[PDB]
Amino acid sequence: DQESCKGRCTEGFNVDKKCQCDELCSYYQSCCTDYTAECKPQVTRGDVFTM
Image 1 (spheres, one colour):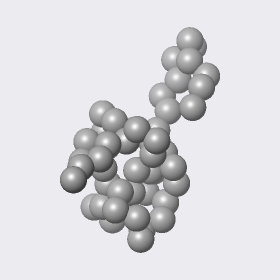
Image 2 (cartoon, one colour):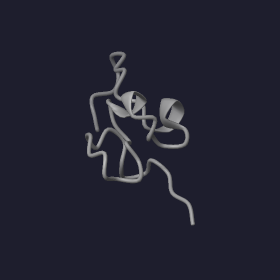
Image 3 (cartoon, helix red, strand yellow):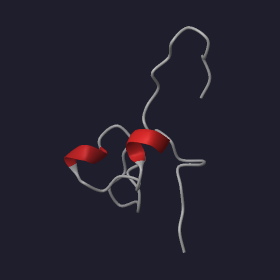
Image 4 (spheres, helix red, strand yellow):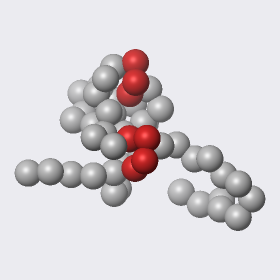
């Protein structure tokens, strides 16, 4: 069995969950398997305003 960020990206911190798919995971080493390319918080540029 396996999962990904789809439905989880920046959901917010709750350390009981199997993925810390959020802003605080680096402090707990409990993040998604590819956080920095799949779950990384918004970095808006001028042409995207949606979550």
